Image 1 (cartoon, each protein chain N blue to C red):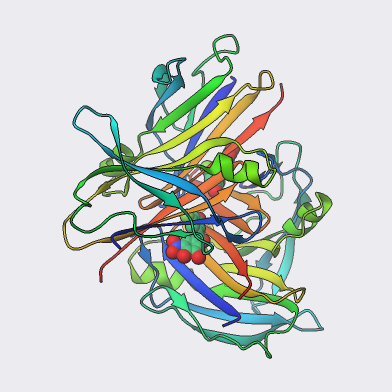
Image 2: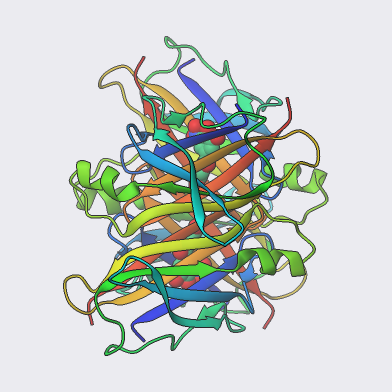
Length: 116
Length: 116
Length: 116
Length: 116
Ligand SMILES: O=C(c1cc(O)cc(F)c1)c1cc(O)c(O)c([N+](=O)[O-])c1
Ligand SMILES: O=C(c1cc(O)cc(F)c1)c1cc(O)c(O)c([N+](=O)[O-])c1
């Protein structure tokens, strides 16, 4: 698993379950092409988005659909989504964990990058 | 000032000065129209982006060039930029402050939405 | 104002108003001596805690009563309080702003340390 | 494992390894008694601090020695330590993950609380 995303709920102190997200890759013509998508599990984690062979050098965007998450809980949040944009595998393959901690009017995001 | 942006540096414990950003408004064809831009001041703040009459309801994106900020400090960053995508809502008067707290491999963002 | 505290509410997207806090200074016997206190204003800020001459180098603790804040909004919180423990340092002049961003099960805190 | 602590480094995008921390419990006379201590592993995690039988109702304090962590990396940080104070097991046994995301002048902390 070279790319894993973990989402936490700072209001309930729980994983953020069933959070949808889309991953895009910047194409040579500078547009965003669809790369992978999925939803977080009961642990707040989304695994298996890609493989080492498919996950080439590039600029990637993770768009986490935080608005739908909060709406289903009865909250009208500030953000449309949490957006994480980063260059990946510039110095060879790495393993990436992207984390997001969600509140209705705020979110934090961090990356843990490890060398296989 | 209906919309202000404040950027802070979590490594130096200081305003993040001379940080460039662009604000976009989502168009009917789901593309991002440039709307305003600028660079943070010595206080880390960017004022005067828009006016009350110009700032209508809609989806806005603030794209903060964090990568250039960290590269100018000689620190390798994770993100290409920090993105803040939100719906501006006109139920009551609203002044928006978008704040971002920057670290090389993480950022936090919050909205302080008040009434004069 | 050598020391100011600002508290924000990540659930409502607003200053955290009427938040009580106490500031302590570590004594020679490793106990916490009360030093100053107050409640945040309508802007979420607490000014006038100390003066330049009183605020000497040492270890300070800011104890923010986040639990009472959330209980007054009817929201069950995780933390008993938010603690910010830091060394005040006199190499150059220094103005300190302690900020805290509150969620029921999470908080962030940062220091913005500037020079007039 | 009813109590686990995870520490991340927001400057390097890595687990925070070999971070010491002490856990205290509030005694009936309102003083802090030592409860458990340890250091984070190569994954940034500290497991096995306590057991379900030992981890009774009470007010607990986790003091994470962030200052020693940053000093060893050549950074002079703002905080003496990160302090997490919370009531545990008030409604029966729970499993607690305490997380801390560290920067030199800022930290975030969150709790994930699950029912066994
Ligand atoms: O967003 C924040 C913020 C973000 C965090 O992750 C943690 C925290 F303690 C504050 C913020 C907002 C403001 O309006 C503001 O003035 C400041 N400040 O000056 O320090 C900060
Ligand atoms: O990024 C974080 C994170 C973000 C924050 O704003 C504050 C904080 F204390 C941790 C994180 C990453 C992980 O991999 C992870 O397991 C967890 N967790 O379990 O709680 C959290």
